[PDB]
Each structure stands twice: as structure tokens, then as C-alpha cells.
Length: 341
DNA sequence: GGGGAAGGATTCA
DNA sequence: CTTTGAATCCTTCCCCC
Ligand SMILES: [Ca+2]
Ligand SMILES: [Ca+2]
Ligand SMILES: [Ca+2]
Image 1 (cartoon, rainbow, N blue to C red):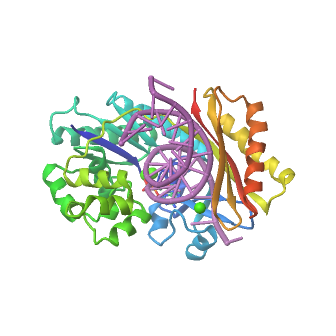
Image 2 (cartoon, rainbow, N blue to C red; image 1 turned 180 degrees about the vertical axis):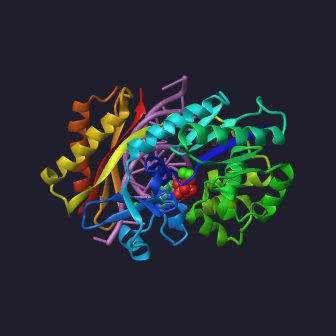
Image 3 (tube, rainbow, N blue to C red; image 1 turned 180 degrees about the horizontal axis):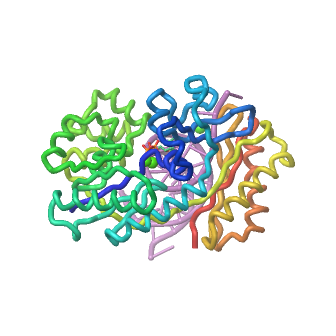
């Protein structure tokens, strides 16, 4: 099959440039402020002008400002980004009915029935890029290959504002020369476990005892990597349906006082119920981040949908359970809804 | 023995 | 004193449907 993956470039920061054109060419840093003190929080994303200097996703705002004190720092406006995203995703549906929106700035299109070979696929990619740029003024990077994993890898290799095809021969080459830590789904934790087994390339996963691999990184990831190594990886492009929606918020001051936490929890519940919109959850989990950054949760599943009134009384019961089964103080508190009707 | 659901922790991004 | 949303993975346990 032929897969065409679209990845919006430094998306949040690019949208802010689209809304304020004079920002282009200047380092722009979109931040997620937490409210614990002046500039507390981290960078959500930065444009390349900022990344060039080390200011990137994940570094503390305070740190970023030490590197680029005169950069433009903007608060994250997720709603705006989500609406621009939605409009771009609609443009993409016009190129294939088989589309998988993987996130706010990523989507896979199965274009097998639209093009005959990679040359045509490439031309369709330029067409898609021109279209998005024309309608929304947003640049994207297109990756094209035989399956979702290599289509994503192609985009990783070509971003920003690029387009790349990874034909069958290059797939075989990558299976031998690509750093396994660069394979989608393999984060830091897994990359290190793999490194401790002397595995640095997909190909390496074949010449090892399966139970040794499975025992180290889990059965699912082991089978996943081996299938990629056997060039036998296959996963169809399917419509994504979110399976859980929730919100967890950092508090003013750590605590284990029920009456003092209710407000924050109820806040997360109202914001969660807003995002649900029509979706009716049968399950609820209360999640707490401890003073020392540990994450603990308690949940419950009901035989029917959970009205917000039910969510309110039940969340307290679940938070009480955590408070009781854990001596530590809570830093962050939130709720998570799932098992939608 | 193993399907399948539920409760939690882990991992990815 | 870095976010923080969501899927994935690991155990346990019921049940023989
Ligand atoms: Ca992106
Ligand atoms: Ca992304
Ligand atoms: Ca833990």
C-alpha cells in the first residue's frame, strides 16, 4: 500500500506567526505557564529560529529566557491551534477517505487507491502542501512510504517544510542503518533498555532470543520491532476515536486537605465535561501527582453513563481513597473519563 | 488454560 | 521547583457464558 503522512511544522508557534506575520523570522516560543511563580512552567514549542539556539519543547521558561531573553514568549492558546488544525484536517479528507488523525498536527492518509506509484504519490504530496499553504498559510512536511511507520520516519527526515519518499530499497537500508531510537513508539525508556542488549538497529532485533527481548521491553514492543525488522509490519489506516478525555491541574500549594483540593478537582471536572461534549463516560479515574512527582490514581466503572452529578460525588470518593491509601501530599490533581457510550 | 474486563502504573509525545 | 493529554502495558481476578 502507499501511505502519505502529514506533519504540521512547529505547529503552535507557526499558527502564532500566521496570526501575527511580523513574528516571522524572529524566535517565537509558545509557553505553558503553571502559576507557581514568575515564569514557572515549560516551553510547549518554539519555531526553528528559537530551536537553533537550544530553546525547545520541554525546557523551563526560566531557562529559555536565559538563552534567548529577547525572544517573543507567548502563552499557549490551544483552542486556536485546535481550530486551525481542524480546518487543515478537513482539507486532507479531500485527498483520501481513509485518513487517520493521530494528533493535533499529524495525520496518515492511505492513498493506495489514489496513486499508482511513488512518483505520483510525491506529486500528490506537493499538491497537498500547496493546498494547505494556500488556504491556511501553514507549511507542513510530507512523508511517503509503504506503511505508517516509514511514512512518519520519512517526515522526520525531511522536516521542516519538506517532502520525502522512502521507497522499498531505502526501507531495507533503514532497517539496517537507522538508529532504533528513532523508530516511532520507541521513547527514551525503551531506547535505553534496547541499548543494554546491544541493539542499535532494527535488524539487531532478529538475532536475539525473543523471550529475552520480550522480557526486557515487553511483548508488544518486541513483536512490533521484529515485524518492522522482518519488513512485515502492517497496520491499516483507521479512523481515530479518542478513548479518554480528562484534565489534571497543578495546585497553588501542595496539600492533603480534602476541602482544599475539591475546588481544583471540580475545576478539572467542569473542563473535562466541556471537552466531552455529548460523549457519555461510563468510567472515571481520579489522578493525583504527589509532592515528589509520583503519579497515583483510583478509578471506577459504572454500568451506565456518568451524569456530572455522579462525577462530582464519585470523584470525591476516589480522591478520598487516594488520600487514605497514600500519606504523601498532593501537588497535582485531576480527573479522567473513558468508556464512552 | 486463557478470554476478557477492570484497576493502576508506565510510557510516549 | 518543567506540561500535561492520552494510549499502552502489566496484574489480578472472575469464569467456564
Ligand atoms: Ca509537527
Ligand atoms: Ca506533533
Ligand atoms: Ca509510580
